[PDB]
Image (cartoon, rainbow, N blue to C red):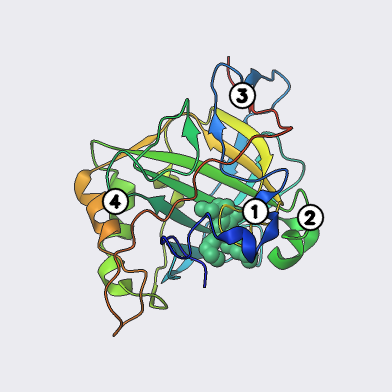
Amino acid sequence: HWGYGKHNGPEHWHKDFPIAKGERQSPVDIDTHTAKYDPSLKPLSVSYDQATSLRILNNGHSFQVEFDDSQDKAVLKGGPLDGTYRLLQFHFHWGSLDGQGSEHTVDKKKYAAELHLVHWNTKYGDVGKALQQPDGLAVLGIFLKVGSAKPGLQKVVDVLDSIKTKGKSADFTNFDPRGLLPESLDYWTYPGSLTTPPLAECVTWIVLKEPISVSSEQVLKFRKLNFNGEGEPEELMVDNWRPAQPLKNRQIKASFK
Ligand SMILES: NS(=O)(=O)c1cc(C(=O)NCCO)c(SC2CCCCC2)cc1Cl
Ligand SMILES: [Zn+2]
């Protein structure tokens, strides 16, 4: 029943998911002058050479590109993490207007969109068990600004008309997620939560400082998606972002000075 409307959006979620008002909720504003450089943080090891994408799905909240996570094939290691995190899926959050759409903000700046690569800690064996642990998931977050097209995004944008409505999926094999990364892996990190219900507090957030540029045509195709299912009234899938939450007793650390 949750969503992003006036009636069912972020200010309502706490009634079904009381952790919404918890101590380590996401997203947050990243105050760049308060984040402390941590010389002990390691470079982020993104190993996506063996990634096996399988499918793309309109889940009614976002669209997601899913991967085979039954073996280490696409993994995130290093940075603030202990151990090995397998890539499950990526999805986006976007706005109705280019001045909004990201969940994390940087000195209160909103980006047009935000990409989340969702990974789970292999020690916990499966993602449902990982959801129950404070170090269960790691999300690599990447900001999108509107300018030049991102060539590595076009295969995704070109299949969206086939998954226009909630519950539609399409085979999506041989997609390389390396094409969605910026040149620099400099990042901020903090302990947080899912930004969508159940808002579980199990995520180590790794947010890249460098945003990727996507064209206005690419983000317009995201805005043609629908939150509704086939044969129901049309509600464009836009503004599917949760606003920044209180930082509370948390420190954001920077990998770079
Ligand atoms: N915006 S986020 O914090 O990066 C995030 C989003 C999703 C996600 O796909 N949410 C849509 C509703 O299920 C998931 S999927 C998750 C898989 C296990 C069951 C709970 C949802 C995971 C994360 Cl970390
Ligand atoms: Zn997300």
Q: Nearer the viewer, mark 1 or mark 3?
A: 1
Q: What element does badge 3 sit on?
A: strand
Q: Are marks 3 and 2 in contact (CB under 8 Å)?
A: no
Mark 2 to mark 4 CA distance (whole Å): 34 Å
Residue at the disc numbered 1: 20
Sequence-first disc among 2 and 4: 4
Q: Is residue 24 above or below residue 234?
A: above
Q: Nearer the viewer, mark 4 or mark 1?
A: 1
- Residue that badge 2 annotates: 133
Gap in Å between the C-alphas at discs 1 and 2? 17 Å
Q: Amino acid at mark 3?
A: Ala
Quadrant of the displayed image that contains ligand 1: bottom right
Placement of 233 over or under 114, stated as above or below? below
Q: Position of residue 148 (x, y in %)?
A: 23, 37
Q: Work out how far the residue at label 1 is from the one at label 3, CA to CA, in angstroms.
A: 26 Å
**Separation of marks 3 and 2 at Cα, in angstroms:** 24 Å
Residue to which mark 4 is pinned: 96
Is residue 150 rendered to the left or right of residue 191? left
